[PDB]
Amino acid sequence: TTYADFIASGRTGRRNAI
Amino acid sequence: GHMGNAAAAKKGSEQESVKEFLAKAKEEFLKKWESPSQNTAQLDHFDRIKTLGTGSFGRVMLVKHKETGNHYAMKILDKQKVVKLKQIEHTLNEKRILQAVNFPFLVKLEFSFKDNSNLYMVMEYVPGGEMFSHLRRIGRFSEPHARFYAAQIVLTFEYLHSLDLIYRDLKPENLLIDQQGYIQVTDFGFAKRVKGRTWTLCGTPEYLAPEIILSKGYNKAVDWWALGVLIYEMAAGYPPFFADQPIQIYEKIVSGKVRFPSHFSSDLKDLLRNLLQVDLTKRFGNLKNGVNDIKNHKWFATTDWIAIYQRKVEAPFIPKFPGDTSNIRVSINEKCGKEFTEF
């Protein structure tokens, strides 16, 4: 599922600007 | 047509009233922009309470004004560390924007000063914290809930863009929820006042418009793309473009394909396809009718734009209730005086 893919992304925490 | 005479006249007059407000808004902004305020407090006016945050250029601290007992979030910036990180113009510009803007959904700079070592920006304190944490906790916001936040962003961008300001860092991490449940936009570190086009590679990967990724010049339409990302993330619980590394996120961003959860309404999907539009000649917010394409969209049909601006709409959520914080040395020698004359 998309939600499971989101979790697996490692990018569920606060995101830094580039 | 879609509107009979009464609805069309009403909408016309509302749009004319917005122009009139924006015109006075620009006038107030430009005065403060051309003559900024400086040195409106000093350090010993405040009690240090708690370090809420720490970063590359300095720290954020909850402070309490000794005279009035009001709490504030004080951004402390090490002048030497700012210089060494090549962030002089960003720091100066951020403070200059904040002291000049005035809008009910923008965090207010209440005081600013500097001493031998540091720069200080004393902001309104928002104890509710970031939208990010509420969104991750609740999972996703229902569409009426997402819409109430989105409307505030639409109004704020309409305001900033009328001042020729591009915001460039929209994300739940930068949206605070105050004690009436309304949004406070924070962190103007990447905002730029520019009428035409600009080129800086900046923003957060998930939220970057394709034309930033593709090294084109770009304009304020990147903020309307970011609005699309934000609305999607609020309503889905996750953003439309993600992967474990930024480069794979950029490939999805430029591909022109987005997928939606099956619980998205058709009105929501239509709005998002028009915001998450790679082709700049078709992106809502960027067309001849400007922001009215967004405000007039079916997904916002129940939105009372004036009532939102006036903060008369009951918020869908109120963070749990001053000073709750759950959910520094000064050289004898002045450092970097010339670089920060304007602060």
Image (cartoon, grey):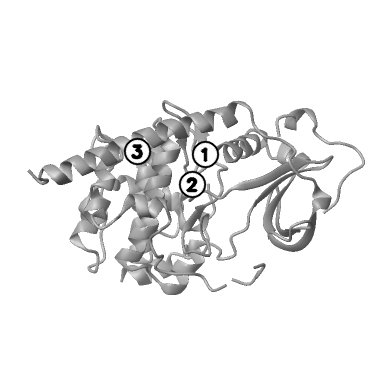
The amino acid marked with disc number 2 is Asp
Provide the chain ID for the residue under circle 3: B
Please provide percent x and percent y for residue B56. 68, 49
Q: Is residue A16 left or right of residue B73?
A: left
On screen, B47 above or below B293? below
Q: Which residue is mark 2?
A: B169
Which secondary structure, mark 1?
Answer: loop
The answer to whether one can see residue B342 in this image is: yes
Provide the chain ID for the residue under circle 2: B
Quarter containing the C terminus of chain B:
top right
Please provide percent x and percent y for residue B55. 68, 53
Q: Residue at x 37, y 33 (%)?
A: B20
The amino acid marked with disc number 3 is Val
Q: Which residue is mark 3?
A: B18
Please provide percent x and percent y for residue B332. 92, 41
The residue positioned farthest toward the left in the image shown = B1
- The reply to whether discs 2 and 1 touch (Cβ–Cβ < 8 Å) is yes
Q: Residue at x 82, y 42 (%)?
A: B117
